[PDB]
Amino acid sequence: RATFGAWDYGVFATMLLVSTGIGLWQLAAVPVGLSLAASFMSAVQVLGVPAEAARYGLKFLWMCAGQLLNSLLTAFLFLPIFYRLGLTSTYQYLELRFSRAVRLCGTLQYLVATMLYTGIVIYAPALILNQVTGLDIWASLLSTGIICTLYTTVGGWTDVFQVVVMLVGFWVILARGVILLGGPRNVLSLAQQHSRINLMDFDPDPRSRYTFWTFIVGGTLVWLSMYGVNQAQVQRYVACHTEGKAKLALLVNQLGLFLIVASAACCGIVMFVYYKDCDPLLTGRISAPDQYMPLLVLDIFEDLPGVPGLFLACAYSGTLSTASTSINAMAAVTVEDLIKPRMPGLAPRKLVFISKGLSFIYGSACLTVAALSSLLGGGVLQGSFTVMGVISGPLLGAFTLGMLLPACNTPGVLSGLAAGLAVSLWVAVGATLYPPGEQTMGVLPTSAAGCGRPALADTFYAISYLYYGALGTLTTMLCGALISYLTGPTKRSSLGPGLLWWD
Image (cartoon, rainbow, N blue to C red):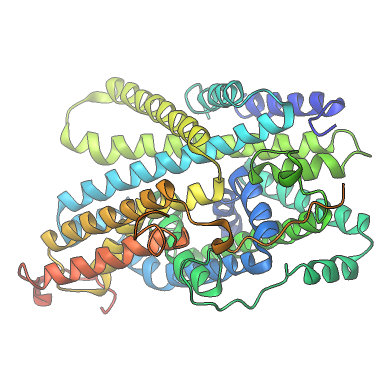
């Protein structure tokens, strides 16, 4: 109990092996959108969103409000620019706007951000395996790395099946939990009593981790960083045979992500009310809050033996498949965008070998980043939203500056990228060397009676992590706006046909 110990071991092993092996032996656009909702279905979200909802309440539902505002700008301000142009890759726009140097810089920033994000995405299934089997945290990470390598290197329509299965799993967990605790009315009343239904939270204090202001502002930009400029996600919409179909598929992706993040938050609330007494953290039954969901599944499905095995094997294999797909994606991007253009004559024999080698190097780098995440501390959702905000925040800032500011020469945008990246790294490192107090973040009390030294660690490093990506972005523009209009602007009369949004 509390760590498999039944047929669930066999079911987990069988499902993992089958997933690893069997991989390789207007509504037509709906699945494509549902394919990009499979990038936020990773075990990262499974572990994070429920735990964060349980610890901070229902405020986490405002994540959807970020999504609903990131797929509303991505489908009306960023998709037309990337479509009316017509681009093999989105970063090509930069070469059309400022110069090839900015294209290379943006590609490097995307590569770094993706490697860190995939490191976290690989760490999450390692956490699942360690919690489920008690197989250390380093042997578990080793096994996860080996399986991911077998996926990406040796070779590798489940993009929608994995979603469907994990979503029905979330709904099943919700139903079972609510049944155990009586009915929806009792659970809702209990959650309300313990201040878990604090949906309306407008406190302006930026240090407050989760709030309406924080979620809207920070999450919108942290989500544009992942689904508005991300080459892998956006590339699927520059080949939809029409702009309207691309927008419809993007809205379908928005709906899928909204459903995922609402089900996860609701199941997190059910988890909390289930553990309203004898909280695992206070009783030592687990180590980190990200070990909440596996524990919830294991405790709940004691009547049905293998269901935890099936659900967690899906959440593990799907997450590794997503990580391997991302690794292959950036391995291909490196060859097509950075290497091949410089070396024109290489022939395919060496190009395929270089692609495989880059996939291997990226896999190893992501595994090392996962090990670093495990060693450094905890937090999978926070880790993802920090790595993808610190790095991919200034990049979105550069895109927005180039679109909405006609007079943005290359030096201005480059210095804006520098300043934004520096500021984001500054705050993200300050908040890890002097983490904010738990009470100030907004963590709610969890009963168990049933069984900043410097001057910038108290006011600056304490901001919610969601603002990190919104802090670089809002600097990359401002600096890039206060330098472009000083180092000589770019007259709009000679800028390009459709590189702007005002046109």
